Image (spheres, rainbow, N blue to C red):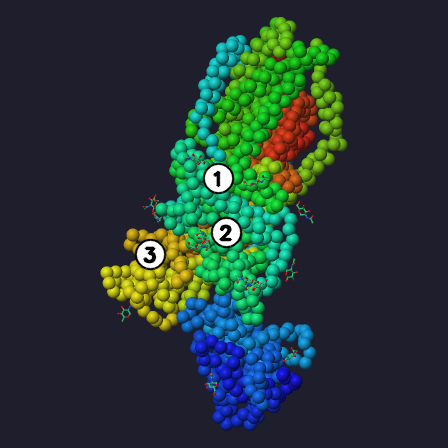
Amino acid sequence: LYTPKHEAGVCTFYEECGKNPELSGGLTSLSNVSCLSNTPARHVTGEHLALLQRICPRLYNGPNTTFACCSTKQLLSLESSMSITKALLTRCPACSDNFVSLHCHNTCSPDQSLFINVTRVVERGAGEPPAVVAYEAFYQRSFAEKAYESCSQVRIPAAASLAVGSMCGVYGSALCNAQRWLNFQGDTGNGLAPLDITFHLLEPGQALPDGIQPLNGKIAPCNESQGDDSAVCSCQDCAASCPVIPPPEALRPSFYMGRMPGWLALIIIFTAVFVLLSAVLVRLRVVSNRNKLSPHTILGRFFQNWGTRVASWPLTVLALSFIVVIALAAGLTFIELTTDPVELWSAPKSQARKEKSFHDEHFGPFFRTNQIFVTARNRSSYKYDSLLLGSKNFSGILSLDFLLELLELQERLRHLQVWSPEAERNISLQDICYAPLNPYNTSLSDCCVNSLLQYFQNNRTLLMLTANQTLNGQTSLVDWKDHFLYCANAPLTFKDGTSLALSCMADYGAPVFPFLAVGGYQGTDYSEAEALIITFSLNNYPADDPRMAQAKLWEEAFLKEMESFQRNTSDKFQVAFSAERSLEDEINRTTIQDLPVFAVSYIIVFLYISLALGSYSRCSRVAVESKATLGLGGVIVVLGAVLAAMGFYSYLGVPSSLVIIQVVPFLVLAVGADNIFIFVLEYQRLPRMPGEQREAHIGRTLGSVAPSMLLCSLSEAICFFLGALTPMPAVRTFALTSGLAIILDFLLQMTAFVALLSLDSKRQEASRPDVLCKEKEGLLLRFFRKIYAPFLLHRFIRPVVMLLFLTLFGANLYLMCNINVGLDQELALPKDSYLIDYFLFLNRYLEVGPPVYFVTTSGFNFSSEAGMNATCSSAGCKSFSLTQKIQYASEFPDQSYVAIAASSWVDDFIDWLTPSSSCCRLYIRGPHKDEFCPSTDTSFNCLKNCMNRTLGPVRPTAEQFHKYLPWFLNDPPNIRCPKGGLAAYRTSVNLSSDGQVIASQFMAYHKPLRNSQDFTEALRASRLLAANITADLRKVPGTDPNFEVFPYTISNVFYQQYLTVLPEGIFTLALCFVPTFVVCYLLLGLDMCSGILNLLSIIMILVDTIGLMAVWGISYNAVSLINLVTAVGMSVEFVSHITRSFAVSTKPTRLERAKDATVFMGSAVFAGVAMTNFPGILILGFAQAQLIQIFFFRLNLLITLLGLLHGLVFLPVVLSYLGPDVNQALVQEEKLAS
Ligand SMILES: *[C@@H]1O[C@H](CO)[C@@H](O[C@@H]2O[C@H](CO)[C@@H](O)[C@H](O)[C@H]2NC(C)=O)[C@H](O)[C@H]1NC(C)=O
Ligand SMILES: *[C@@H]1O[C@H](CO)[C@@H](O[C@@H]2O[C@H](CO)[C@@H](O)[C@H](O)[C@H]2NC(C)=O)[C@H](O)[C@H]1NC(C)=O
Ligand SMILES: *[C@@H]1O[C@H](CO)[C@@H](O[C@@H]2O[C@H](CO)[C@@H](O)[C@H](O)[C@H]2NC(C)=O)[C@H](O)[C@H]1NC(C)=O
Ligand SMILES: *[C@@H]1O[C@H](CO)[C@@H](O[C@@H]2O[C@H](CO)[C@@H](O)[C@H](O)[C@H]2NC(C)=O)[C@H](O)[C@H]1NC(C)=O
Ligand SMILES: CC(C)CCC[C@@H](C)[C@H]1CC[C@H]2[C@@H]3CC=C4C[C@@H](O)CC[C@]4(C)[C@H]3CC[C@]12C
Ligand SMILES: *[C@@H]1O[C@H](CO)[C@@H](O)[C@H](O)[C@H]1NC(C)=O
Ligand SMILES: *[C@@H]1O[C@H](CO)[C@@H](O)[C@H](O)[C@H]1NC(C)=O
Ligand SMILES: *[C@@H]1O[C@H](CO)[C@@H](O)[C@H](O)[C@H]1NC(C)=O
Ligand SMILES: *[C@@H]1O[C@H](CO)[C@@H](O)[C@H](O)[C@H]1NC(C)=O
Ligand SMILES: *[C@@H]1O[C@H](CO)[C@@H](O)[C@H](O)[C@H]1NC(C)=O
Ligand SMILES: *[C@@H]1O[C@H](CO)[C@@H](O)[C@H](O)[C@H]1NC(C)=O
Ligand SMILES: *[C@@H]1O[C@H](CO)[C@@H](O)[C@H](O)[C@H]1NC(C)=O
Ligand SMILES: *[C@@H]1O[C@H](CO)[C@@H](O)[C@H](O)[C@H]1NC(C)=O
Ligand SMILES: *[C@@H]1O[C@H](CO)[C@@H](O)[C@H](O)[C@H]1NC(C)=O
Ligand SMILES: *[C@@H]1O[C@H](CO)[C@@H](O)[C@H](O)[C@H]1NC(C)=O
C-alpha cells in the first residue's frame, strides 16, 4: 500500500483512472487523479513525443530514447489547467515556462520515484490499481528558491500589483516566499488544488533522510536569453537585470583650502607674524647699543587740580552722583525678558531663516510633539507558535495585561480638560489638536495620536477577540498577536487574511508605521521590541495668537498626569516622558536655583578688601583699623554702575535675559574692583610732609595713578564694544552692557569714591572709630624687596624662564588644533531632571531621526510630459529622477543621513489616474453628467473612465491634469481604491487660483542622531543632495532661471552656525587685539616697544588658554566665546600697569629699572587682581550645575593662573632685556625741579 522502490527508472503512477472521490463540492474543473502503478517507465514516441517536446523541451532526450510516465489525456488536462497561470504571467514568458516546467516534470518525469514518495492509498475498485489521494515530494532549497526568484517581482498585465501576490493565498506579496507559495499550490483547502502534495525544502548541505536524492534541474535566469529570441525580462519585471549604481565615494575632511590642510595655513600665517614683530624689537635695541610738554605732566597736573577740587566738596559730588545713578537705574520698570533658548542662541538673519519663512508661509507651521516611552521592569521573553508565521519570540512588554492598562492611560489623556481663566472655560483636546483630516468641524476621534493600539482602533472588545481557522492540515485559534504581526509588515491594508478580518488603519484615517509605534528592535523582528511609544501632536501658531496660551495650559495637565501615573506604577514598568515646552521651563529653573550662590560670592569679596586694606595693633583690633567703609563703598559703586547700564539699555528698548543678569555683575566686578584697591594702596604708601593738607595729598595721589586707570579702562571698554559683532543676541547684549558698564564705573570711581576716601581720612585723623561700632613697612614690600626680586632677576635664571615660556607657547600652539566644537543640551539640565532619563531613552530605543522635507519652489512646469518624466519614477522615467535619487541615497544611511525613502505625490497621482484601478470615474447619464463620481458610489450610473485605455506609460494632458488634480487631493482612501491624497498629500501641494502649482514637498526620515556632530553632518549631507537635485532639474527647458529646492527641518535654525570654516568667534577674537596696541602706543608717547610687548604678551596668554582648554576637554561654543572675550579684557590688568610703570622710570639702566617696577607695581597688582579674583571663583564650586562648573569655575581658574604666570614672571624678564629707553624729558624735568 506504498511504493517499495524509489531508486531510478521506475515510476509510481501512469494512467488516469477517474475522478477524486474524497473531494466533493468543488464544482470546478479538476484533473482526474491517477491510481498507483509501480512499474517501469513507458517509451514515448510519435505524436505523443511531439506533444511532450512541444510543451516542455527539458525532458527531450532524443528522437527514439525518450521515456516518460504520463499519458496524452493527462497532458491535455494539464494544458487546460495551466493555461490560467500561463495567461497571468504574460509579462516575461522566460520565467513562466520555468513554473510550467515544475508542473510537467512532476507529472511526466521518467525518474518519478527518486523524488516522489506516495503516502496515501484509497481502494477505488476490486482487482484495480488503488487511487492515491496524496503524496510527498522532495526538493533542494537552492533550486526552489532560485525558481521562485525568477518571477518573484513580476507584475500582472495591469502593472499595479505583483503576480506573486495573487498566488500566495491569505496574504499578498508582502509576506510570501518559496515554501509558502509551493504549499499554496498543493493545498486543496483553497478549492483549486486537485490533491495534497507535501513540499520538503531539504537543505543541500545536510542529507538527513537516507535513500532519497532531492532534485535540482535546469533553471533559466532573467538575463539569460533563450537562444536567439532576445526577449529577456526587463528589469522593471524581475530587477536582476538592472544596472549597478556605484556606491558614494569618500569625501575629504572639512576645513581645507588650496592644496594644504586649512588649519596648517593658519599656524604658519600666525607664527610668521609672531616672528616678524619680535625682530623689530631686537633691531631697536641694537640701534641703542650702537648709538650710545610730555603727556604725563599734563595728565598729572589736570588730575591733581580735579582731585583736590572734588576732595574739597565731598557732599555735593556724592549727592549729584547718587542722583544720576538712581535716575538711570529707574529704567528697569520697562524690562522685557526673552526666555526661548533658540531665539537667544541663534543668528537672526541667515539662509535658514529665509527657508523657514518660506515654508511657514506656504505650508503652515510645524507641529508640536508630546511623547512618552514605557518599558517593562521585570519579565521574561516567551514564545508563541502561530499557524501563519511559526515560532516567534515575544518580549515581556508585549504581554496582554499591560496593553489594557496602557489603553486606560491613553483614554484618560484624550478626554482631559483644563480651566482657562481668560476664556473662563474648559479647554478640550479637539480645540487645539493637530489633525491631518477634517481641520474644521472636527471631533475628538480625528485628533492625531500614534500608538500600537491604533492597529485595533482603540476598541477594547476587538483586542480580546479570538477565532478558529484551518490552514492545510492544522486547525487552531488566532488572536491579537497574529493581527499585530500581520499589520506590522503591511501597514496599509483594509482587512487581514485571517478569520479576524479587521482593518489595520488608524481611526483618524491614516496608516501607522512600525517605527512610530514600537522601538528597540533590530531588522524586521518587530515582536522582539522592548519599548512602547505614545505620541500626541498639537498645532503650532503665531506667537500673537491667544490660542497658544490655551495649548500651553493643556501641556501642564499632561505633565501632572504622567507624574501621578509614575508614582502609581512604580514597580511594574519604567516610564520616560516629555512635553514640548519642558526644555524652555527646565533651563530657566536652573538659573533661579543658582542666583543666591552668586550673591554670596559678592559679599565674600567685600570681606577680603576690609582685611587687605586694613591694619592691626598686635592682635584683635579689627573694630578700629579694618576698612569696612571702603569695602562697602567700592562694592556699592560698582554694582550701582552695573544697574545703571542695565536701566539705560532698558530705556532704549533692548531686551535681555536671565543669563545676562546672572553673569554680568560678576565679570564686571572682577575687573572694576582692582582700580579701587590699587588707588587705596598707593594712598596708604605715600607719606606727606608737615604743612600739607589731606586734600593736596589726595590730589597728588590721583595725579600719580590716574593715567594707568585711564589707559586700562579705555582698552577694556573698546575691546568689549568690539565684542558686539557676532549676530547671536545673548553675546551682543552681553558685550554692549559690559562696555557701557565699565565706562560708567570709571566715571564714578574718579568722583564719588575720591569724596568717600576724603571723608574716611577726615574721620581717621580725628581718632574716631568707623560707624561699624606707626607707618611700618608692610610684609609684601619687605618680601618682594628682599626675597623675590633679587632671585627672579638673577643672572643664571632669566634665559631658563625665557626658554620655558617659549616652549610652552609652542606646545600650546600645536595643541590648539584639537578643538571639540558644539553645544550639547545634556549639560544645561540639573543633575536630577527627568529630561535626562528622557534623552537616555531616546538615545537607546528610537529607531528613526527627525523628518526632513525637500521643498520645491515655484518655476517648474509639472503639467508637461518633460516635467512628469523628470520627477516620478514609473516605467518610462529617467534613471536618475528626483524620487530615484532620494531612494538611492536612502540605501547608504551612513554616508548620507537618510534612512527611509521619500514618498512622492506625482507617482501616487499617476497611479490613481490608471483606468484599471477604477478610481477616477464619471457619471454617464442624468443631472450630474461629466461630474466627478466618487469611488464609493455603487450605482450603475457611472461606466466611463477619466482616461481612455492605452499602452505603455500613462500621461495626462494639461487640461486633464489641471482639472483632475483637485479631485485627487481630496479623495479619502477606502477598500475599493487604496490610493488617494487626502490622508497624505492634502497639504503638500499648494495650488493657485488658475490651477498652477506654487510649491510642493517630498517627505523623508533621517537615521537616528545622537549628538551635535551628527546633526551637523546630517545638515551637510542633506544640503549636498538638494544641490545635486536642483543642478539637474534646472536643465529642463521652460523652467525659471531661479528655480531651486531646499531641505527644511525644524532643527536647522540652531545648528547652521557650525557649518563654517572658522567657528564664528575667531574673526571677532582676532579683531579684539588691536585696541591694546593702539591705546598703549598712543597714550605712552608713540613708544613702539611698549605697544609691541603688550600685544605679544596678550597673544601668548590667549594661545595658552585655548591650548589648555583643548587638553582639559572643554568644548568651544558661544559661552566659551563670552569667557574668552572676558579673558582678553582682564589680561590688560596684568600687563599694562607693569608696562607703564617700567616706562615711566628715571633709573639709568634697564636692569635697575625693572627691579623697582617689579617690587612696587608687582606687589600692588598681585595683592589686588589675583586675590580679588580667587575668592569669587572658588565659591562657585557649589553651583550645582554642569554649565557653570565647566565653563565658569575651571575656565576662570585657568585664565587667572595663566595671567599671573605671564604677568609677574615672564614680563619682568622680557622688559629687562628688550624694554624701552629712558625718557630724557622726564630726566630734565626731574633735575630742574630741584
Ligand atoms: C499657498 O501659498 C500662498 C502664498 O501666497 C498662501 O497665501 C498666503 O497665506 C497667508 C496665510 O493666510 C497670508 O498671510 C498671505 O498674505 C498669503 N499670500 C498672498 C499672496 O495672498 C496660501 O495661504 C497657501 N495655501 C494654504 C492652504 O495655506
Ligand atoms: C467596538 O467594537 C465592537 C465590536 O464590533 C462594536 O460593537 C458592535 O457595533 C456594531 C455597530 O454599532 C453593532 O452592530 C454590534 O452589535 C456591536 N457588537 C456588540 C457586541 O456590541 C463597538 O461598536 C465598537 N465601539 C465603537 C465605539 O464603535
Ligand atoms: C475553537 O475550537 C475549540 C476546539 O474544538 C472549541 O472548543 C470546544 O472544545 C471542547 C474540548 O475542550 C470540545 O469538546 C468542543 O466541541 C469545542 N467546541 C466547539 C464549538 O467546537 C472552541 O469553542 C472553538 N471556538 C470558536 C470560536 O470556534
Ligand atoms: C507647461 O507646458 C505645457 C506644454 O507646452 C503648456 O501647455 C500649453 O500652454 C499654452 C499657453 O498656456 C497653450 O497655448 C498651449 O495650447 C498648451 N499646450 C500644448 C503646447 O500642448 C503649459 O501652459 C505650461 N505651463 C506653464 C505654467 O507654462
Ligand atoms: C540652547 C540650545 C541647547 C537649544 C537647542 C534646541 C534644539 C537642539 C532642539 C529644540 C527643538 C528640538 C526638536 C523638537 C522636535 C523634535 C521631534 C522629535 O521627534 C525628534 C527630535 C526633534 C527634531 C528635536 C530636535 C532637537 C531640537 C531642534
Ligand atoms: C475524468 O474521467 C471521466 C470518466 O471518463 C470523464 O467523464 C471526465 O471528463 C474526466 N475529466 C475531468 C473530470 O476533468
Ligand atoms: C514514504 O511513504 C511511506 C508510506 O507510503 C512511509 O511508510 C515511509 O516512511 C515514507 N518514507 C519517507 C522517507 O518519508
Ligand atoms: C545576470 O545577472 C546576474 C546577477 O547576479 C549576473 O551575475 C550575471 O552575470 C548576469 N548575466 C548576464 C548575461 O548579464
Ligand atoms: C522580578 O522583579 C520583581 C519586582 O520587584 C521582583 O519581586 C522579583 O523577585 C524579580 N524576579 C526575580 C527572579 O528576581
Ligand atoms: C526565539 O525563537 C527562536 C526560534 O524559535 C529561538 O531559536 C531563540 O532561541 C528564541 N529566543 C529566546 C530568547 O527564547
Ligand atoms: C470643567 O470641568 C470640571 C470637571 O468637574 C467642572 O467641575 C467644571 O465646572 C467645568 N467647567 C465649566 C465651565 O463647566
Ligand atoms: C492607581 O490608580 C487607580 C485609579 O486611579 C487606583 O484605583 C489605584 O488604587 C491606584 N494605585 C494605588 C497604589 O493607589
Ligand atoms: C519622456 O520619457 C519617454 C520614455 O523614456 C521618452 O520617450 C520621451 O521622449 C520623454 N519626453 C517626452 C517629452 O515625452
Ligand atoms: C476616448 O475615445 C473616444 C472615441 O475616440 C473619444 O470620444 C473620447 O473623447 C476619448 N476620451 C479621452 C479621455 O481621450
Ligand atoms: C551628483 O551626484 C553624482 C553621483 O554619482 C555625481 O556623479 C555628480 O557629479 C553630482 N553632481 C552634479 C550632477 O552636478
- Quadrant position of the N terminus in the picture: bottom right
The kind of residue tagged 1 is Glu
Question: Helix, strand or loop at disc 1?
Answer: helix
Task: Decide: is 875 above or below 491.
Answer: below
Q: Earlier in the sequence, mark 3 or mark 1?
A: 1
Q: CA distance from mark 2 to mark 3?
A: 38 Å
Q: Residue at x 64, y 48 (%)?
A: 378
Residue named by callout 1: 555
Q: Which callout, 2 or 3, points at the residue further toward the start of the chain?
A: 2
Circle 2 or circle 1, nearest the eye: 2
Residue of label 2 = 460
Q: Please name the residue shown 43% across and 40% down the image.
A: 428
Question: Helix, strand or loop at disc 3?
Answer: helix
Q: Which residue is mark 3?
A: 966
**Drawn side of residue 157 relative to residue 249, left or right:** left
Q: Residue 789's x, y, as percent?
A: 72, 25
Q: Counting residues from the N terminus, which is met first, the one under dot 2 or under dot 1?
A: 2
Q: Position of residue 1093 (x, y in %)?
A: 61, 32
| Residue at 55%, 21% in the rendered image | 638
**Quarter where residue 1098 is shown:** top right
Mark 2 residue type: Arg
Pick whichever, 544 or 212, lies toward us. 212
